[PDB]
Length: 50
Length: 50
Image (cartoon, rainbow over all chains, first blue to last red; front, side, top):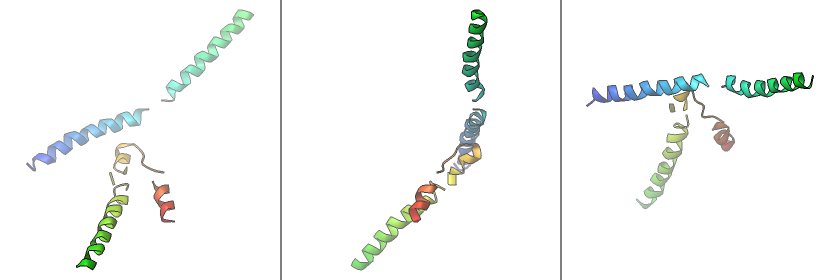
């Protein structure tokens, strides 16, 4: 049994690591995009009006 | 004995807040560790002690 808790907390925690891992990983790259396509669309309107 | 009852109700109540400001503290910083954040507590409780 107390082999036992040595492992389970270990597999659980191993998992929290991945949770951290995703947490480390987070977006600005994404936020960037809407701004750009919103911007490119506008230049296209230029060229078109030109 | 009687008198002794209020004394424990005080020690009760207190180990309970301290268990805990001790719990807003471990495991908050446990996360950190993996990567999360618990903290504007303090600001709560710090201004609370003030």
